[PDB]
Image (cartoon, coloured by chain):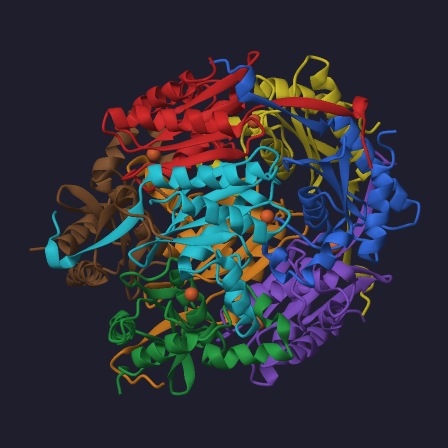
Chain colours: A cyan, B brown, C green, D orange, E purple, F yellow, G blue, H red
Amino acid sequence: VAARGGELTQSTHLTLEAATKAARAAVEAAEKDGRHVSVAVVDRNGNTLVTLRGDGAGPQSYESAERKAFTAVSWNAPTSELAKRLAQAPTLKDIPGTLFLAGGTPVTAKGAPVAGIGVAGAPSGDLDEQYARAGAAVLGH
Amino acid sequence: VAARGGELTQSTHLTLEAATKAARAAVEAAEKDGRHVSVAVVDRNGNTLVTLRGDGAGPQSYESAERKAFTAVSWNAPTSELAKRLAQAPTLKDIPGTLFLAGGTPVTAKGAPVAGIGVAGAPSGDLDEQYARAGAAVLGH
Amino acid sequence: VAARGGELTQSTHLTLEAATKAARAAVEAAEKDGRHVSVAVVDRNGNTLVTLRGDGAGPQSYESAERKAFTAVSWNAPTSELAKRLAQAPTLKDIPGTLFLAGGTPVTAKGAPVAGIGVAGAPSGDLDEQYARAGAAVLGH
Amino acid sequence: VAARGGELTQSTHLTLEAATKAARAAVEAAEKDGRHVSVAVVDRNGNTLVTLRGDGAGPQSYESAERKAFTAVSWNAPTSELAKRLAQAPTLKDIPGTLFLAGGTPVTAKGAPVAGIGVAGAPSGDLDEQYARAGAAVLGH
Amino acid sequence: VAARGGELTQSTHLTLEAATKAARAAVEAAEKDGRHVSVAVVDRNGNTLVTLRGDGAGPQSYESAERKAFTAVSWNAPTSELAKRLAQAPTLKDIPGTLFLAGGTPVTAKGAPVAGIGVAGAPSGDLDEQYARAGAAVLGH
Amino acid sequence: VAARGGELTQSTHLTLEAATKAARAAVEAAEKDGRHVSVAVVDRNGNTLVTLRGDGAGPQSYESAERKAFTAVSWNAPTSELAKRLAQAPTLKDIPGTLFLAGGTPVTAKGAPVAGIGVAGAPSGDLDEQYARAGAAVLGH
Amino acid sequence: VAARGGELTQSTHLTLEAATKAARAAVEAAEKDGRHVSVAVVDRNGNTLVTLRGDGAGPQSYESAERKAFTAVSWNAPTSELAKRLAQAPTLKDIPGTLFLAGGTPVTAKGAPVAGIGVAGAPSGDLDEQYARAGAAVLGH
Amino acid sequence: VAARGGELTQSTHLTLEAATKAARAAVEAAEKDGRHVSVAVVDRNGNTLVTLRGDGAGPQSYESAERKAFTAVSWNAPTSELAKRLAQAPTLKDIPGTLFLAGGTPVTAKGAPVAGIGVAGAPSGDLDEQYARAGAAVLGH
Ligand SMILES: [Fe+3]
Ligand SMILES: [Fe+3]
Ligand SMILES: [Fe+3]
Ligand SMILES: [Fe+3]
Ligand SMILES: [Fe+3]
Ligand SMILES: [Fe+3]
Ligand SMILES: [Fe+3]
Ligand SMILES: [Fe+3]
C-alpha cells in the first residue's frame, strides 16, 4: 500500500555520522578542560540519535544531557536562553521531557531545527553549553 | 549553527492530513460493520501522528491500536504476518513497544515504510486488520 | 449480570466525530497563521479521544497538548486562567497529569465540562489557546 | 463553549454507591471462607471506581484485582473465560493493562458492559471469581 | 521457617472495615454540599487501603487524593499544615509520592499515625480537608 | 484524631535487625562459594526492607532478587515451587511485580508469612534459593 | 572477546561490606536518638548498593534516602550544601533522579566520590545528614 | 570523608573511546550489508555508555539493542546462546531489563565481563549478533 505525493511530506536530519561527529567533538572539548561530561544528540522528532557517557561523568549527567538536547531542539534555542523564559512563564518547565538548564544548543538546516546537542556534568551548565557549541561547530561546515 | 548537505539526510512522511484521512477511513469501515475500534497512525520514526478513540470502544483498545501501528511500521508488514514469526522466534514479543497481534498494517512511500495504521477492539484482530487495510486503501492515489 | 435503574447513572461526552471535527479546525486555524502545533481532545473522564500531530510541530508539543486538555476539563476553565491560580496555591501543579499553561480550553454541555481541547507548539501559549478556542468554536451550535 | 445535541452522546455507569456495595460484598463473601482478598471495581471507560485492600491480603493482589476488573469489562466476559482464548490467540495477554486470569467478572446495563469487578488473592482464581460474582450478585436486581 | 519472638515486631493499622467507613463518610460529607470528590485511605506503610471515585469527580482528583493521604500519614500532620513547611524548606515537595496541598489528614492510634485520609476535587483544598476531617470524625468513638 | 480498639488491627513483621542479619547471611553463604549475588528482604506488606548488591553481581540481579522476595512472601511459598504452578496457570506470571523464578523463600511467624528472602545471580536460581534459605536459616531462632 | 589494556579504565568503589557497615551505623546513630529513618548507599555509578528501612520509618523515607544519596555522590557535596545552589540555579532540581534536600553526604576515595549516603525521615533534613555523617564516619579510618 | 583501602575495591571498564570504537564498527559492519541498525554499549554495572541510532533503523531497534547489550553482559554470554536457556528455565525472560534475543555479545577483560554490545534491526537477530561480534572484534586487540 503506497502513498504519493501530495500526501507525502519531507523532513531534514543529521546523518548518524554527523551526529556522532558532533557528539564526539563535544566530549573532546570537555576532555580538553579536564571535564567529565555526558553528551546527547536528539533529533527534532526527537528520538535520541547518539549518547556518549564520558569517563568519570556524574551518573545524573546522562539523562540530563538527553533532556537538554530535547529542550534545545524543541524550541530552536539554547537552553541557557530558554531558562530565561521561566521568569514570565514558569510552567514551561512542567512540559514533559524538558530540562530548562544551560547545556543544550540547537543545530539547524536552512534555519529550521534538525537536532539538539546536550551536554551535562561540567562545573556549570554554561560550561556545558560551551562544549555543546564546540560540538555544533564541527558541522558542517 | 548550520549543517549542510553531506551531513544532512531526508526522510519521508505522511502529512497529518493524509494520516487523519486514513485513520478516519478505518473508523468508518469499522462502524460500517457495527464495531467500535480505536485507531492509531504511527510514523516510521515512530511518533504517533493520529489517534482516534471510537465511541464505545474498549478502554484497552487505545494503547493496543498504537502498538499495533508501531509494530507494523517497524518491520514493514501486517501484524498478522508478524505474529507468525513468534513460532520460530518467541522472544520478538519482548521487544519494548510491540504488539504481535493482528490489526496493524504498513504504509509505504517509494518502497520504504513511512507509517503504520493500527486498529484495536473489534471482536478479533483479523477484523481489526480488515479495517486497517481499508484505512490504508484511501491512500494515495 | 445486569444492573437496573437506580444504581446506574449517566454521563455526557463528545462523539468521536465531534472531537475530531474540533481538533482538525484547531490545526486548520494554526496552519492559517503558518503555525505548527499538536492538538489533543481529552474527555471529562479524561481518556484522550483525539490527538493530531501537526506537520513540523515540536516533539514536546504532543504530550503538552494532552496535559493542557486534561487540565482544562478537570477544572472547567482555560489553562491560561488556571495558571494564575498558582500565585497563592503554588502546589496545584504538583497534581499528577496536569499542565498549567495557556493552550487548553474546556468544552461544555449545559454548563458541565465534557471535553478539553489542548494546543501546543505555537510561539506562545496564548496563541495555542486561541487556536484551541477556534477548535471549540465549530461546535456546533 | 457549548456543544448541542447531535454531537453529544451518552454513556451508562455504576454509581459509586453501587460499585462500593458490590466491592464490599465481594470482600464479605471472601471473608465467609476465612479468605483475604483485594477487590477493585473498574468502569468500562475504565477508570477505577473502587479499591478495597483486604485485611491480610497478599501485597500482589491489589494491582492484580485492578487488572482483572479492567480485563473483564474490556471484553465483556469473565477472565476465566478470557484466559482460555490464549490457546488460539496467545498475544492477547500482551495488550497493556490486562490480566488474563480468573477473578474478574463483568457487570452490564441492558446487555452492554459498564463495570468490571476484580478479586485477587484467594487460594485460586476460580475462587476469586466466585467472590467477584458474589460481588455482582447484590446488583441490581 | 519461623522467626520468633524478639526480632518479630508489631504495627497497628486501621481495618479495611474502619477505612471504608471513614472513606464513605468523607464522600457523603462532600455529597451533602453538592460536590464531587475522590477519596483515599492510605496505610502508614503506606499501601493504599481504600479508594472511592465520586460520580462526576475530576479525573485528576483520584491520584491527587491518594498522594494527599500518603503525605498526611508520612509526617503525621494535615497536608494544609505541611504545605506551610515549604516556605523554609521548598524541596520537601520533590520527595517522591508526596502532594503538599490541603485535603489530607492523619488518623492516629495512641498518638502515632496509622493511616492518612485524602480528599481531592472540591473547589478548594481547604474544603477537601474538611471532608477528610469529616471522614476521620466517624472514628472512634 | 485517634481510633480505638476494634477498628484497629495488628500485623507481625521482621525488625530491620532481623531482616539485615538474614540478608547478610545470604550474601555470606554465596560469597563462601565464590558466588556474587544481590539479596532483598521484602515485607508481607511488602515494602522492601533490605537490599544488598554484591561485589561483582550482575546488574540484573538487584531487581530480580527484589521480585523473587516479593513473590515468595505473596503466596507463602518458595518461588521454585511457585514456578511449577505456571504449567496449569501460565498467566500467574502476568501478575505485576512478580518473578516466578527460583531464589525466593518465605519467612513465617506463627505460620503466617511476614517476609520474603530473595537472591539473584548465582549460576542457577536453585543455587540462589540455597543461599536464600541459608539467609532465612539464621532466623529466628 | 578480550579487551586490553589501553581500552580499559579502572574505577574505585566501596565494597558491600563497607557500604553495609556505614549504612548500619547511620541507622543506630538515629536509633540512639529514638528517631526512625531509612538509609541508602548509592555508588558513584550510581547503582544503589544498600538500603535499610528502619522500624517505624515513614513510607516516604525509603526513596527519599535513595535520591539524597544519589544527589550527594553526583556532585560530591552534602545535599544541604547542594540545596543552596538552587537560589541562583532553580532548575538544577529538575535533573532526573535528584533530591536537593539535606540528608545526603558524599564518601570519597583519594578525593574523588565513590558513594553517597542518604538518610531520610528525621524531624529535619539536618538531623538526617547528621546521622548520614555518622554513617560515613566508621569509614575508613 | 575518605574511605581507604580495605573498604575499597576496583572494577574494570571499557573507556568511552573503546566503547565508541566498537559501537561504530558494529554499525559499519551492518552498513556494509546495506542494513540499518541501532547499536548500544552497556557497562557491566550496566549503565549504557554509548548508543547510536542508524539512519533508517526501525524505531523499535534502539531500546532493543540496549536490552540485548544489557542481557549479554549480565550473564557473560551471547544472547543467542542465552535464549536457548528458556527451554528449561522459561521465566528467565521475566527478569526486568532483559531481552533474550540474538544480537547481544559480551566483552571481557581478563575473562570477566566488562561490557555488552547490542545490535538490533537487521533481517534477523543472528545477523544483528554477527555485526555485534564485528563491533567486539576491533577491540583490543
Ligand atoms: Fe547534570
Ligand atoms: Fe485490543
Ligand atoms: Fe509545548
Ligand atoms: Fe494475585
Ligand atoms: Fe484535585
Ligand atoms: Fe537474576
Ligand atoms: Fe523524607
Ligand atoms: Fe529489534
The C terminus of chain B lies in which quarter of the figure? bottom left
| x, y percent for residue D59 | 62, 45
User: Whole-percent x and y of residue B42?
Assistant: 28, 52
Q: Position of residue C126 (x, y in %)?
A: 42, 78
- Judge whether H39 appears above or below E32 on screen: above
Nearer to me, E103 or C6: E103
Q: Nearer the viewer, residue A126 or G81?
A: A126
Snapshot quadrant of residue F138:
top right
User: Which of these two is toward me, A110 or G95?
Assistant: A110
Q: Is residue A126 left or right of residue E114?
A: left
Residue at left offset 68%, top offset 21%: F131
Asked if residue B138 can be seen in this view, the reply is no
Measured from the top left, where is residue H4 in percent x and y?
A: 81, 26
Q: Quadrant of residue C116?
A: bottom left
F113 with respect to G54 (left or right): left
Looking at the image, which is closer to me, G94 or C70? Answer: G94
Residue B50 occupies quadrant: bottom left
Q: Exactly how many numbered labels are in the figure?
A: 0
Q: Quadrant of ligand 4?
A: top right
Outermost residue, left direction? B141
Q: In the picture shown, does residue C113 fall above or below D49? A: below
User: What residue is drawn where x is 38% and y is 57%?
Assistant: C59
